[PDB]
Length: 148
Ligand SMILES: CNc1ncnc2c(C)n[nH]c12
Ligand SMILES: [Cl-]
Ligand SMILES: [Cl-]
Image (cartoon, rainbow, N blue to C red; front, side, top):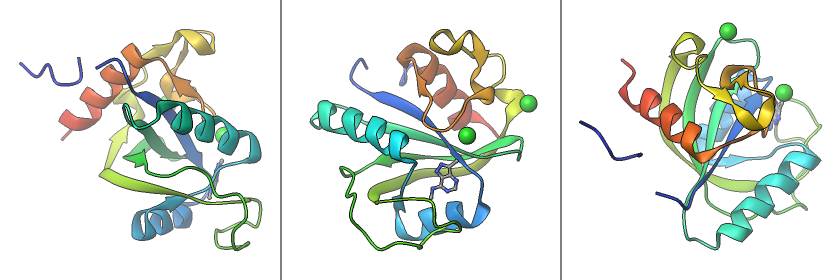
């Protein structure tokens, strides 16, 4: 048995990227930036955690059909940073991450996990910074960890 992920202090978000280059840049430099509303959501979760648990980010390129890895938020959002460092000049700010898992996990492995906070929709049909309920997040993380 693996009862590791089966922990009450942690919050988990879906991150969608239109750009594969932005994924590569995030992995190389351990940074990210979301939309205005996404940054606001992630910053609030990180700050309210107060280091009592992780904020996990489940990354997936839009249209790719798979998740590509898992990172932990590692700083609050700095909203005043160099512009234009990502593929599109649509993002304002920066925060630190730590990629802890880089591997492709097909949507077929995850699509039976549904989000009660998003109309029972499959977790694989989420938009950027959709939050995942912790009990569903534990199921997702266990599947990502054990996929081969
Ligand atoms: C740098 N951050 C990003 N890059 C490309 N796409 C997205 C989305 C949909 N949210 N944040 C994104
Ligand atoms: Cl699908
Ligand atoms: Cl999206």
